[PDB]
């Protein structure tokens, strides 16, 4: 389908346990600016980013949400473009499990929060900017999806991004296609 | 319901 232009890895921990690595493929030709923001926050380039932040909200059979590195509760985060930035486009959809999309507070309020779907979420199409998909590591996404949460859907054991970074792609490549 | 928002979490 769309072409992967850059990859990003996250090493996750659930409570006191190293659980594995997730590798994302990002669609920099489709949504260049939303991809640049995510990659810059994964490398910590501009002095702030995702390393050591938590996934604050996970709901089984829906998605896992993270990226609030300032407040850690869903109300914070910021982008490399300022505190919030506009919706770039809605060309890609939440096609099935493993797609990565921007969380927001309505139209044009993207910051740093994102979610990874664990099911197709067609009701979010056209309202959230989709910009990448999990290439490797869907089984560690399912382990975070299954952690116990309290009644506010917050993990009882902290799910931490212990390390993260960019992996260069020399030739953009299409995802498995149909 | 099943939304993914940042600030006012809804049903």
Image (tube, grey):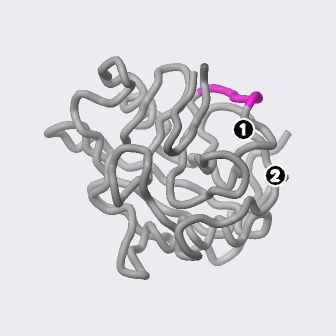
Q: Position of residue A79 (x, y in %)?
A: 53, 68
Q: Picture quarter containing residue A94?
A: top right
Residue A90 image point, x, y percent: 81, 51
Contact, mark 2 vs mark 1 (Cβ under 8 Å): no
* Residue at x 18%, y 39% (from the top left corner): A17
A166 w.r.t. A128: above or below: below
Image quarter of residue A42: bottom left
Q: Is residue A90 left or right of residue A110?
A: right
Distance between the alpha carbons at the discs numbered 2 and 1: 10 Å
Q: Quarter holding the C terminus of chain A?
A: top right
Where does residue A35 sit, x and y in percent of width and height? 63, 66
Magenta residues: mostly which secondary structure?
loop
**Occupied quadrant, residue A73:** top left
Mark 2 residue element: loop
Q: Which mark is residue A94?
A: 1
**Is A129 contained in the magenta span?**
no
- Name the mark nearer the viewer: 2 or 1: 2
Q: Is residue A120 magenta?
A: yes
Residue drawn at point x = 55 percent, y = 64 percent: A7
Subunit ID for the residue under disc 2: A
Residue for point 61% across, 46% down: A105
Q: Chain of mark 1?
A: A
Q: Please name the residue that numbered disc 2 is placed on.
A: A90
> What span is colored magenta in the figure?
A119-123
Instruction: Decide: is A94 above or below A38.
Output: above
| Above/below status of A101 relative to A169 | above
Question: Residue at the spot x=56%, y=46% of the render?
Answer: A134
């Amino acid at each position: 389908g769309p072409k992967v232009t850059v990859k990003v890895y996250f090493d996750l921990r659930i409570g006191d346990e190293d659980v594995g690595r997730v590798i994302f493929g990002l669609f920099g030709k489709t949504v260049p600016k939303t991809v640049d923001n995510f990659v810059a926050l994964a490398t910590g380039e501009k002095g702030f980013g995702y390393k050591n932040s938590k996934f604050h909200r996970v709901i089984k059979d829906f998605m896992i949400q993270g990226g609030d590195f300032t407040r850690g509760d869903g109300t914070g985060g910021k982008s490399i473009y300022g505190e919030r930035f506009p919706d770039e486009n809605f060309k890609l959809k939440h096609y099935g499990p493993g797609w990565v999309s921007m969380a927001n507070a309505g139209k044009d309020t993207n910051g740093s929060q994102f979610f990874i779907t664990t099911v197709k979420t067609a009701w979010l199409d056209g309202k959230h900017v989709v910009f990448g998909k999990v290439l490797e590591g869907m089984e560690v996404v399912r382990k975070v999806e299954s952690t116990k949460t309290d009644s506010r859907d917050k993990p009882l054991k902290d799910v931490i991004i212990a390390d993260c970074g960019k992996i260069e792609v020399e030739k953009p490549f299409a995802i498995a296609k149909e | 319901x099943l939304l993914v928002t940042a600030g006012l979490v809804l049903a």
